[PDB]
Image (cartoon, each protein chain N blue to C red):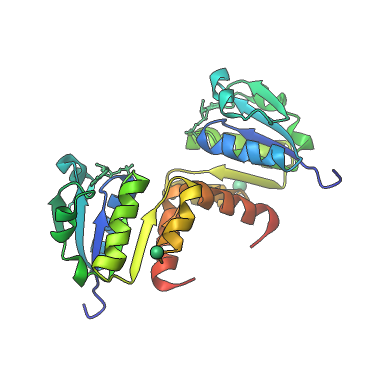
Length: 137
Length: 137
Ligand SMILES: Nc1ncnc2c1ncn2[C@@H]1O[C@H](COP(=O)(O)O)[C@@H](O)[C@H]1O
Ligand SMILES: Nc1ncnc2c1ncn2[C@@H]1O[C@H](COP(=O)(O)O)[C@@H](O)[C@H]1O
Ligand code: NA
Ligand code: NA
């Protein structure tokens, strides 16, 4: 399950595969999207869910994911512009409330957050954790 | 500063250089250690502080850092065994209270933490942040 959610993850790399594998083992319905079919070898033997090969910077790829049914969308490619494209479409075309994007450039965080997209910026996250260990929290 | 601390950072890569540059701009005394002299090109023009070339898996390198004077030691190489060596020496040979290590393998976190070493494990940190965005926290 009654708690099962519909989750779309773009990017089946190091980050995306980790989240996909965990989401699947938690009982969610998971769609994982990558431009490179070989990326899917990171999904483990237990992964239940569906794969989609396509370039997520193309609207037609976004249409093939059933994103209007999604509870959450994760924009986890290695390109900030692509993740912005995915996340803006998720929010506004497909009306997804919970959208999380990876953002490498800290200066790009603001434009995502002003559009209601939650951000994971590795540099910021590491600095925040160091600060907690020095100054408290 | 009167607030200036003595900070030793091992590994001048992507993570270490970011912390070194920020520490220096905050007014701290910073020693940065790397086996590869070319790594120091990541330090910015404003960086004040000292560099040490050496293999941090060798005790003689650890002796050249004045670690018994350190307020904090950051074990930020790309090798978990090396970071354990550095951190254990920092804690117990050089009596540093505040020691932070990067740990890639989540299964290795426990042995660091049982020895009073704070850990930054990228995979764990990313999963924790995703969880906060879904479940709150
Ligand atoms: N335009 C795109 N559409 C879909 N997947 C992409 C796109 N650009 C990059 N990726 C994927 O994002 C992933 C990034 O991997 P990593 O840096 O390990 O998280 C790789 O598997 C890439 O093939
Ligand atoms: N045994 C070691 N002693 C000192 N520096 C090291 C050692 N092993 C790796 N490193 C450095 O740690 C850094 C890791 O870089 P990065 O993966 O970008 O954080 C590099 O600049 C390496 O040369
Ligand atoms: Na807007
Ligand atoms: Na011990």
